[PDB]
Length: 126
Ligand SMILES: Oc1ccc2c(c1)OCO2
Image 1 (spheres, rainbow, N blue to C red):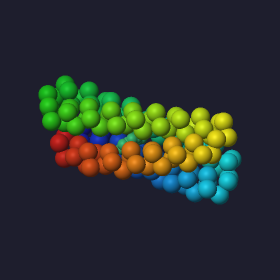
Image 2 (spheres, rainbow, N blue to C red):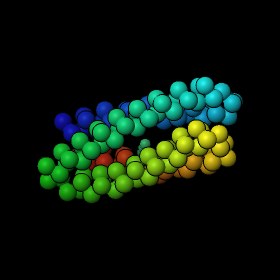
Image 3 (cartoon, rainbow, N blue to C red):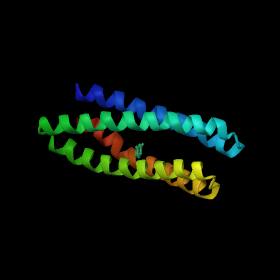
């Protein structure tokens, strides 16, 4: 069902949170080789999450689940903010700009946390 597909999408999201937190520790410790690998892994996870989310929104639309569509439109917009900040973080890493990396890292944490009440709201609406 779309609800089990959203639970699968939620788990992939949690996997990104887990990897993100081990990447943050690695960054703080200066282990740039680990950071590079974690950033690649996070890219894959975010790409996968985004794909699952679009499939869930499209299905909600085909099902005429207006409330779910509203919430998913808001959530996917927030997800794109996160993606843009993530890509800026990756660029800051490439450039060796640790001050920008620190900034972007904090911002991505705030975007992800704020989206969680909505994320929980979607689970109930599908
Ligand atoms: O990759 C993400 C970017 C922004 C988010 C998110 C995941 O869940 C809540 O908001």
